[PDB]
Amino acid sequence: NMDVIGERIKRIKEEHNSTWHYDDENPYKTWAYHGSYEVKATGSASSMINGVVKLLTKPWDVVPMVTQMAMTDTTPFGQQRVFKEKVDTRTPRPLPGTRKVMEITAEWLWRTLGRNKRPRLCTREEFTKKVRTNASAKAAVEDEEFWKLVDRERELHKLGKCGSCVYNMMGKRGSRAIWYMWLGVRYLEFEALGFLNEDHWFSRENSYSGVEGEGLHKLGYILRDISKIPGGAMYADDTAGWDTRITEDDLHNEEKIIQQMDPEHRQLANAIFKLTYQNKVVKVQRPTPTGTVMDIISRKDQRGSGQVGTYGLNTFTNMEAQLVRQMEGEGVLTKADLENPHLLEKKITQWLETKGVERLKRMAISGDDCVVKPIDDRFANALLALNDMGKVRKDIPQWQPSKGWHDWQQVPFCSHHFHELIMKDGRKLVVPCRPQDELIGRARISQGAGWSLRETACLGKAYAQMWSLMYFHRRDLRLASNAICSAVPVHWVPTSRTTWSIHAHHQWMTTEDMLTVWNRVWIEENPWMEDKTPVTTWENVPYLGKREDQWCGSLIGLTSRATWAQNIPTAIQQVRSLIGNEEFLDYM
Ligand SMILES: [Zn+2]
Ligand SMILES: [Zn+2]
């Protein structure tokens, strides 16, 4: 194992020769520990509050979920706590028959996903464009010396060696050299595996089960379309710590995509798979009585959560795992088959070739998140292969049948559920939703410290406009959104981001009129909206039924909420007076 990771550790140990030591009381049980060195503490025990959103959401000052979200611990203490809970475990090896079905399915699945698209290398110019369009990283990309280090590392990869590709459990911390090595490792991963994302291999059209690039505003419509397929209930089982359950067998199956690559691409992707996925060197902060140390650890399995290929590879493995579970529910795979090291291939290949694509269409898969509508309910108790592959469901005994839903509107997916609304004109909309306290709690969080009232107000406007576009059907959020937009100067451009979710298309990151953007998203560009008649007033943009809004957390009907609603122009004026003599519009 040291032959692949040795060079990386040597460079770290040499760079930190002053404080390098082997801490005898390191807490690592399933990860190989190499040593430690002193570091300045990274992270915070609490999150900074967005004063603009807080001032305009006074009734949520008395709400428990809002307080919890403001309490994210990212300090070395917090890092170690999560590590012990989840990360420091071993997944039992799947049985020989299970490994055979997984291999057959992975091979068939990669061929299916590659039917129209050819893998390709991604470029310095693409990486540069993505870094620029999103936004330290933008500065590194402009530096020619960053790219010469990338070239030097790439030459080692071509030789089957790695010198600087090290993953971090936290954030960035002589200082530009360590940062260039991190961003350079992300570039090389992007160059070799970025095609999965850049060329939309997991789009619904390409992958059948995937939803990559679809967007939050389409997810509900996709669940409603799956609901029309004849079969059993819709299942949406949560896996306990999916990334920790990715096995050596899963990684071997994922690597199969290299077979479809050109020789020059295959060499680079083979280097990413072998040196950074199947072997990894990780940095993790740890508090000590003396201060704070950085631990250097390694392992041969599990998924690195913050990697370019993580989303696509998790989606791939979950599509494979759910097809295997569907085969088991259908009686194609028995307990005897899973234990069998001489399992017959024939029935598996026949099911995949005749039913595979149809079975993929019964699913919505996004990383570890899945919804499956199997042909019948035998799937509920078909748990042998699911547990054996290591994808053990969260907070339920291993062998208790899964509970499915007979209404797509009750199905959890991507932290949301979806409602069908009827507009005043009779047209139907399918909208995303979640418990309201989660939406308000998140909008009240400002990421980082040392932010002016301007940057704070602009992030507040970004949240308000996200509510106008995605959660307009929630009475309190439409009201709060109108209040925030009335308090923030009309010409101020929303900055930073409301979410890192892959489903977010950030249509709210604009100073274009929100009703114009709403019509474009929900009417004009909506493929499930046959009648393109525009909505000319917010009065014609619908709400959830009052009862559903309350079931989803609305404060409508409470006296404190009626008080807030009555007194909102006052709070808006207070924000305006502190911002100054700028141009404001009254959205109330
Ligand atoms: Zn490397
Ligand atoms: Zn809801």
Image (spheres, rainbow, N blue to C red):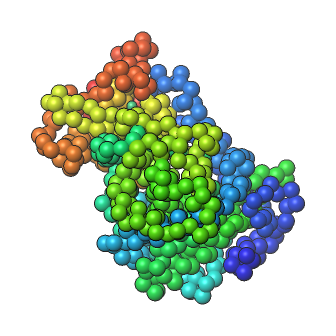
Instruction: Determine the residue positioned at 42% across, 36% down.
Output: 405
Measuring from the top left, give residue 488's x and y in whole percent: 35, 36
Q: Position of residue 230 (x, y in %)?
A: 31, 44
Q: Is residue 460 visible?
A: no
Residue found 82% across the figure and 57% down from its top: 26
**Rendered image quadrant of residue 93:** bottom right
Quadrant that contains the N terminus: bottom right
Q: How many marks?
A: 0
Closer to the camera in the image, 376 or 537: 376
Is 172 situated left or right of 517 in this image? Answer: right
Q: Is residue 374 above or below residue 427?
A: below
The relative height of residue 141 versus residue 335 in the rendered view (above or below) is below
Please say whether residue 265 is visible from this viewpoint.
Answer: yes
Query: What residue is shown at x 85% (from left), y 53% (from top)?
Result: 290
Compare residues 418 and 458 and report the one nearer the observer: 418
Pick whichever, 78 or 374, lies toward us. 374
User: Which residue reaches farthest right?
Assistant: 24
In which quadrant of the rendered view does residue 490 lie? top left
Q: Position of residue 466 (x, y in %)?
A: 36, 41
Left or right for 398, reference 364: right
| Residue 219 horizontal/vertical position (percent) | 35, 46
Residue 73 in the image: above or below residue 437: below
Residue at image coords 68%, 58%: 92
The quadrant of the picture occupied by the C terminus is top left
* Quarter-of-image position of residue 427: top left
